[PDB]
Structure formats: structure tokens, C-alpha cells
Amino acid sequence: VQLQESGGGLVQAGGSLRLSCAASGRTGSTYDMGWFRQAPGKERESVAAINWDSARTYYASSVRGRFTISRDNAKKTVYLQMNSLKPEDTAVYTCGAGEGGTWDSWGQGTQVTVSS
Image (cartoon, rainbow, N blue to C red; front, side):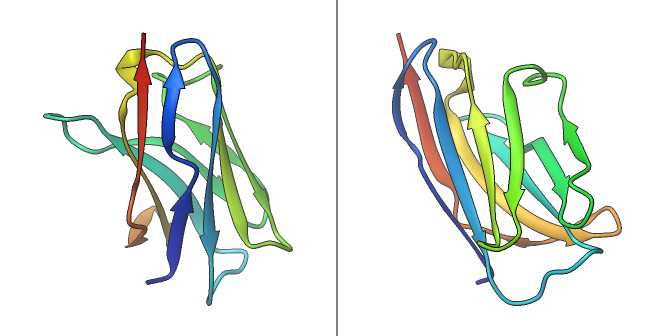
């Protein structure tokens, strides 16, 4: 395993939650870190990604303007700040890593349940 998430849990609609993904062993300027989500009965989808060296970000249209991805080089951790959560955001959020537009390492996933 190379990645491990933390932070999932129960959240009231409209609230915020921060997820973390700690990376270990093998990083550098050519790698990208990303967050994906899979709602029950749905296909896994990208949520956000960030380049380790430049901090260049990408946000899927679904969460654009509400989620913020950042990375702490010293702690080798990537964070996903989720605001204005809706029940429709309930899903297992997973972190991944890769380079060259390819994802090859995955975390275990963390559950985020947003209720009314």
C-alpha cells in the first residue's frame, strides 16, 4: 500500500468535512494525487487532482466551487476540503496517485454520509 485516507464520517447537509490522504515512498515533481468517489450503484468518478510539484489543480464540474484540494509537501499529505455538502455527495471517497495522466496506486477508501 502507498496511500491511506482518513476523515470520513457523518455530516449534516450544508456542513463541511476535510479528508486527508497520506502518501509514503516515491513522490516527486512528476506525480499527481487525486480524489475519486463512488456513490452506491454508481461508477467511480474523479473529483479533484493536484500536481505535487506545481500545485496545479483540477476539479470535476460536479464539485467545482465547493471542494478545495491542497497538498503539504513536508507532511506528504493531500487534503480535500468539502463544503456545502448535499445528501447526493454521499459516497466512498478514495485517493489515488499516478503520473502521465495514469492512476496506478489506490487507497482503501473512506465513507462520507451526508444526511438531511
